[PDB]
Length: 169
Length: 169
Length: 169
Ligand SMILES: O=c1ccn([C@H]2C[C@H](O)[C@@H](COP(=O)(O)NP(=O)(O)OP(=O)(O)O)O2)c(=O)[nH]1
Ligand SMILES: O=c1ccn([C@H]2C[C@H](O)[C@@H](COP(=O)(O)NP(=O)(O)OP(=O)(O)O)O2)c(=O)[nH]1
Ligand SMILES: O=c1ccn([C@H]2C[C@H](O)[C@@H](COP(=O)(O)NP(=O)(O)OP(=O)(O)O)O2)c(=O)[nH]1
Ligand SMILES: [Mg+2]
Ligand SMILES: [Mg+2]
Ligand SMILES: [Mg+2]
Ligand code: NI
Ligand code: NI
Ligand code: NI
Ligand code: NI
Image (cartoon, rainbow over all chains, first blue to last red; front, side, top):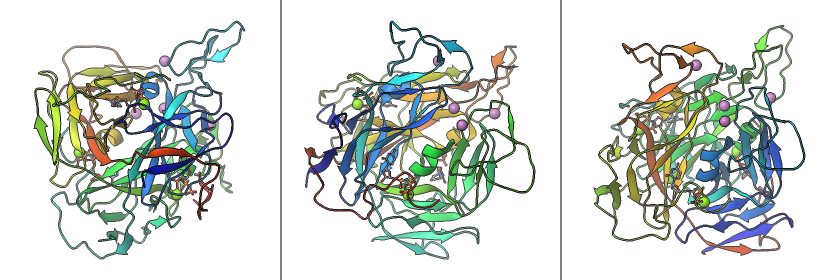
């Protein structure tokens, strides 16, 4: 089967979309408008549910555009096969709280939003509007075998136990 | 073969466990109790070694529960095939050091731990107990081809060189 | 085909290299020498272009050595199939700006670099030299199906809607 079951949970939800024909992931739309202060953490609702078949995992991960330009950090979520719940974007405004005020909010383009109302926000605060693409869903196959406890492994590897920068830099 | 060789390195080690029948990763137990101050970095030992077969990679990655609730950031580790060493959780308490004291430590549920002894900890400090699931192991297949230097690619793509938010937002 | 098309864009570019025979990723060399202050963000050029075939994604991701030892955080980039552009390492010096001076820069080994010239740098500043391996490219297969809007999914899963630490910890 070359089909994925996607369910829209609300009117605020929008169906994921792939950018180019040969692209890896389906861009994820935010279902809610959230303002994030420096160091603030949140799980942004997408109101989108998927039925990933067995033997596959969905990687709910950040986009290079938003991530490189803004301080919004998204933890790559491992969407289990059969997770029929509301996909949540595990997010954090990783900007430092230097404790000085500003009068502008910052959009996902790192640009200061222009508004007629006068407000005092914390510096580094971001606004994410409903319907904006802040994430993407890359679905990769997995290998889930039966685990086996052993005293020692049947063969020696060229790597051995070497890791964490054992080679040069 | 539908079997993975797992070796326990100590009595503090516990064998990885999959939550649901169709889930993606095997939950990783911590083999040591560590207290992490704000901004502090560590590599937490699991005392668990795996023999991943050739053509596959293990993704030693964070769990959504711990990551969304706490300031503990785990870098997704790429466990090479044949790495027979001690799996280390590349971790950081990404909480800001605002330089004010507290009398409670915070567990992996972001709750303040109750204890009879009186101590002064830094605000944002986390305690990770031995035997607690803070990570998971998702094993995905890989494609390792022979690299080839070319003057130019044989075909043009619809994407071209476009990237880093070349589409909208 | 067991071949990947790699193009070098400049004399500063170096072709990716795999550490061990059975390793997952090809180590990525930096094409430029960059000094990163605390909290500073950048996209480091590699001057290396790849032609990943359809049905695969490249994961431009951090190395365990550099990541665990330094404050340099690299966001795992999802290199689309047919992205013929300059691979950019989405990086950030996630070290806290505590606003105190130092006279040494810090290399990717977290060691203070010795130099005859006297300068005042910010504490937590890192220097990344041209030709140093700070990243790696792990290529995994993907599953890009045709999406389908449904009122409800055809079957019930044992997981259901449970997530974000629904099991224990
Ligand atoms: O979080 C991690 C990451 C890696 N590892 C192990 C698995 C892997 O085989 C090894 C190093 O992986 P990488 O090649 O990705 N990092 P690095 O290039 O720094 O190590 P080396 O120089 O030995 O390849 O360390 C962990 O135990 N935990
Ligand atoms: O770290 C990275 C991430 C991506 N890239 C490249 C590869 C990919 O094909 C392209 C953008 O990938 P994404 O679609 O995941 N991010 P975004 O949606 O912001 O870019 P676009 O809008 O062009 O799709 O940039 C890098 O060179 N380095
Ligand atoms: O960013 C995310 C991450 C996960 N999820 C969903 C998908 C997955 O099936 C579920 C939890 O995934 P994990 O098993 O990796 N984390 P955790 O172990 O904390 O949840 P549980 O205890 O329920 O397994 O939550 C999201 O919606 N967004
Ligand atoms: Mg995109
Ligand atoms: Mg789990
Ligand atoms: Mg390496
Ligand atoms: Ni800034
Ligand atoms: Ni930070
Ligand atoms: Ni807090
Ligand atoms: Ni330090």
